[PDB]
Image 1: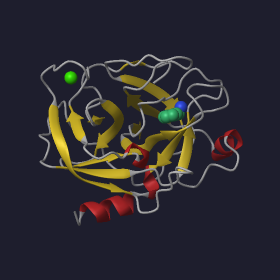
Image 2: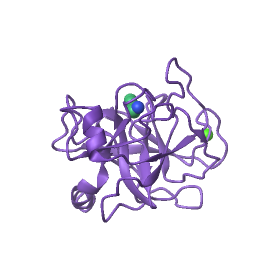
Image 3: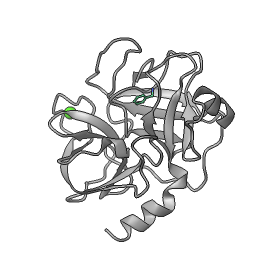
Image 4: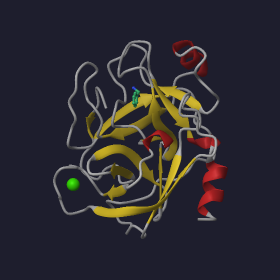
Length: 223
Ligand SMILES: NCc1ccccc1
Ligand SMILES: [Ca+2]
């Protein structure tokens, strides 16, 4: 997250870190057994880390649970990033408490202009590299579809939305991928892609979760 703020420990209780020996992507806990992330975060050998603030210090509220199954969306296209969504099943159920909690799936798609909360442990610099140890947060509005399509001509599908600031300076970044975009208390986006971080006229692009609720619910009911 570039241009954000320190969230505060366990104030984003649905945020997870995906670990393969090191943090590599975020995700969101949607019930006691299942995490949503980005398909482009797929790896074999994922451990899900819940209850984290500092990812390099064991602080006492963590739960570390290995994945038993990953399911990339059937229509994921890694070239275009269309359908950039993946479900991860935990080997055992998480213990839900005030520091580890699920986020609800949406009923309706969020509206342009709504302020959302984006969070992660990704790079904090627009130019250069600095990775934080504690969770960072950013408030950013959903942009109009016409603004989004003008920023990325020929590249925006109906399964994507843009959020952020056309003037630059505040954005998600590398290492935030797969993490949550929460608007009005519901999971509306997944950190997906963009052109760099916090550059002018190049806002972040997010997977539009409201288009996938049927697939999520069917998949959970069968696995
Ligand atoms: N600035 C959007 C973004 C997010 C994740 C990875 C790359 C770019
Ligand atoms: Ca920790």
